[PDB]
Image: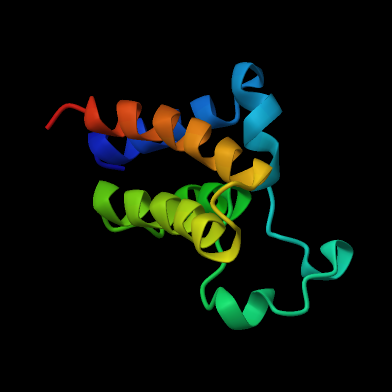
Amino acid sequence: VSEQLKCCSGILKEMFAKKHAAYAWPFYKPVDVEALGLHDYCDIIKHPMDMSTIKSKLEAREYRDAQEFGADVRLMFSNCYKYNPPDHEVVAMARKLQDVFEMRFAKMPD
C-alpha cells in the first residue's frame, strides 16, 4: 500500500497494544447489541464501526487513503459519544483511546 496506509496499520496496532487495553477493549469488536440489551442502538447509530472491522478493511486494502481510515476511526468514537451520556464510563475510555489515535495520526509524515 501507500506509505501513509502502512502507517495507519501501525496506528491501529498501537491501539490494540496491551498498554492501552484497559480502556481500548470496548472498541475491539462490533458493539454486540443483543449481548448488551441495546434495543435502540441500531436506530441511533446508523453506521457502526469498531477496531476489528477497521483492521479487516486495512487487510483487504479497502481504504483509498489515510483520510478514509481516519474517518472510520473517528466514526467509531463519534458513535460512542453520540449514543452515551457524556459522563459515561465508556465515553471516558473513548477519549483516552482517541488521544492515542489523534497524536499518532497527526505525526504521520506527509
